[PDB]
């Protein structure tokens, strides 16, 4: 009988999200950096640098100066999101220079080696790791391992890309590893021992990394003393081998022939935040999983960086 | 020459938003309320209630208890947005009951008047207003004007919809009023004297509302003592007449025949937040306009609620 | 959410379906729940009117029974005794379907001779797993499906997580490893309410005369024709909340968000 | 008027079986037996055995 405009017998209506909301933010970090193999101290040496993409360094947490609204967006979107899934992490190194330190007498001058390249090793085929102590240590310029190289005179175990200056090196990862409608519970990405999604089932006893690195996840969540959630998933295995930046090993009269690279390293980490529903539901933690991370009191802690995953034909 | 995978001579690349990002949040507020014309005090009287949609009450600021993540979403999205545009404001009143207070002896009993209706007046055709003192005053249950009715025995000046119980009354507004790529500068919608977008060019001298109510906007922004922005737009005019809820005026033996309505009032305010760019740009205020609002020291302040806008055929 | 589908709220409501179930549980090694059909019929909507003092009841045909799903909220059901399972007396303090501030409930609205039906899919299990039978004689046992939320006070166990891990004694000599993937379920709190209508005195009081019909489809997988105690290997303990707790809180999670790949 | 989901004016409904239910069980008995006509006593004799079906 009601004659008004846009009036209808009510259906079943409650308008609240029910968790169906999702936001895609891209945290992106772009740096023109000094990659220096010349110096004798503090990760300036011939030692091949390491890009700790296995770690949450994608935030640029190596330094606070590199914060940007993408982090701040992420941070906020984490407060208002119950869970997040990482989509694709796009790393692009641009080489703006290749520079050699030449010796004359004594002191050195730097000359342009355009015509040489920057080496990007994947450190596949080896079981190796990244020590992580402080977020500073995450700096891919100073991050090193002793007695380490991309070049072995005996068995050269590294698959090494080779980059001319204005040639660009891009890579992309799929962090979509999760399924069964699970997510990752948000953090601000403010720790260096948290790691990217994907399962490197290797974990040290010294720093138990936990169930998030195994295909079959089992974990609990306090989320209050009264209730506890059982988070169980199947997440495909990932390898994420150690990615190094190196100069060529070239034997000068004196010693290894020293270079320094001026690069720009661009990151885009696609993050789909699944927003807290329009009504309080603390139990959405049920679907989230703790960020994959390595725990323990250890000051220095070793990121697994497994070479690869073999495949079997059925 | 560079042989690596996914390598190409760089193009012009900086990855930062440049303001192109936008988020659509819907602040939605859903209340099962007591709409009471029976009482003798404090907006419980025969006086027709007013839905102050002209005001920012869409937040539900009438009471803090009605806060929800949509506000909290909005609040955050306002911190990280340089400007916002309102899209469509969907108001839906559901009537779950129509109740009359019958007199017996003395005391009253309430009986179901299913078969009568709730009146929604638009108070068009009249120049009338809404006094707003406190956000509480925004409550559409208690919000009233003295010597006021939807029924004049002489000239009945109101276009009054009439709502059966389980019939629903819905309305929608277009707050897209702005153009020339202008936005509104965000607020948390935490004030009752801020008003919806759209131009009611009427403003009192007592409380200058300002240029946002005129088609041709002119205003300045401090945004630092060093720089100032000139915000100038053309925004189509809006009317937004006073929307009242009323009971029928029915003369019992004693006096006006008293009812009370149990309704649910649902709001959806579509808000497209335009996110702060990935790099600091304080001058995006240049494109935003102050939320339309009525200023001044006035404790009580009158919302224009113009009836309509005449049209001329060229 | 509870095993009240048996009608365990009262013994008087036992019927051959239970007795059938009971027996079929003795002779079945495992059971899978199929579909649980709940139908509320409203035969009356009645208001208590005040006169003077004492009350009379008048027919409010023209008002409705509210069925809330209590979605969008994290809420629970305290369960102490099977009696407490009675949907007539089962309540939470300071609780309503109506909030003057944010109304968080999706509430169906039922005329008298209109009927409210719902159906659940308890087929949650897979990998050829079942549930190990019980007579459904406990109130703290719960329906299949995974609400991963469990209190520390009453550990509910692995049956509420997608990835199940549990062991079975089934004799001191052998033990079974039961491991599954069961899709997640929400099963939000389902309330019956009257409208909140403010009379002169106080909230305006109603009473509903309803009929509530339940059908719980149960496929019993019968004990094989030869003794095989190890079929427990495929069964999983009925999902339940353990612990010494007298009162115990059923999770009743609102919902489950979904992510687009 | 009732707007809820899966709601309809009731028909005549009582859900009880009314005896319409039936179960087929097969009792099956399988034996590797000694059928002996040799012995001199207790049904072991030349006497033809009987299957008391």
Image (cartoon, coloured by chain):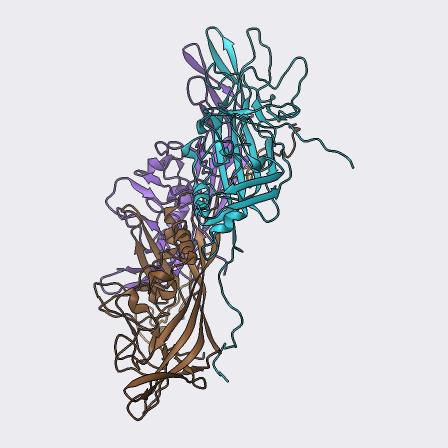
Chain colours: A brown, B cyan, C purple, D orange
A88 or A170, which lies in front?
A: A170
A174 lies above or below C253: below
A114 or B239, which lies in front?
A: A114
C69 or B13, which lies in front?
A: B13
Count the numbered circles shown: 0
Residue appearing at x 47%, y 27% in the figure: C208
The reply to whether residue B274 is in sight is: no
Task: Locate residue A237, reporting x and y percent.
Answer: 39, 70
The reply to whether residue C244 is in sight is: yes
Lateral position of residue B222 relative to residue A121, left or right: right
Task: Locate residue B119, reporting x and y percent.
Answer: 60, 23
Quarter holding residue C4: top left
**In the image, farthest residue toward the bottom:** A253
Quarter holding residue C94: top left
Task: Locate residue C136, reporting x and y percent.
Answer: 36, 46
Task: Locate residue B226, reporting x and y percent.
Answer: 45, 48
The C terminus of chain B - image quarter: top right
A265 lies above or below C239: below
**In the image, farthest residue toward the right:** B314
Quarter holding residue A107: bottom left
B74 or B17, which lies in front?
A: B17
């Amino acid at each position: 009988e009601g004659y008004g405009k846009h009036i209808t017998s009510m259906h079943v209506r409650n308008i609240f999200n029910q968790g169906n909301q999702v936001i895609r933010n891209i945290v992106k970090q772009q740096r023109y950096e000094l990659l220096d193999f010349t110096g004798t101290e503090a990760g300036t040496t011939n030692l091949p640098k390491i890009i700790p993409y296995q770690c949450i360094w994608w935030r640029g947490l190596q330094n606070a100066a590199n914060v940007n609204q993408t982090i701040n967006n992420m941070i906020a979107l984490n407060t208002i999101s119950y869970g997040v899934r990482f989509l694709k992490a796009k790393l692009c190194i641009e080489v703006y220079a290749v520079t050699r330190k030449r010796l004359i007498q004594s002191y050195y001058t730097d000359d342009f080696e355009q015509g040489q390249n920057l080496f990007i090793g994947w450190a596949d085929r080896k079981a190796e790791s990244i020590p992580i102590t402080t977020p500073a240590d995450l700096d891919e310029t100073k991050l090193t391992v002793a007695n380490t190289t991309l070049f072995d005179a005996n068995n050269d175990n590294i698959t090494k890309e080779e980059v001319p200056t204005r040639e660009k090196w891009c890579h992309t990862w799929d962090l979509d590893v999760l399924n069964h409608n699970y997510l990752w519970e948000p953090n601000n990405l403010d720790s260096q021992w948290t790691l990217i999604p994907g399962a490197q089932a290797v974990q040290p006893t010294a720093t138990p990394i936990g169930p998030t690195y195994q295909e079959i996840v089992i974990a609990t969540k306090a989320i209050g003393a009264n209730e506890s959630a059982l988070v169980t998933t199947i997440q495909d295995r990932r390898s994420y081998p150690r990615l190094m930046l190196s100069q060529p090993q070239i034997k000068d009269e004196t010693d290894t022939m020293k270079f320094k690279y001026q690069i720009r390293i661009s990151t885009e980490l696609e993050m789909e935040h699944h927003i807290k529903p329009d009504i309080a539901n603390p139990w959405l933690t049920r679907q989230t999983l703790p960020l994959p991370a390595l725990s323990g009191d250890g000051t220095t802690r070793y990121v697994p960086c497994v070479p690869y995953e073999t495949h079997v034909s059925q």
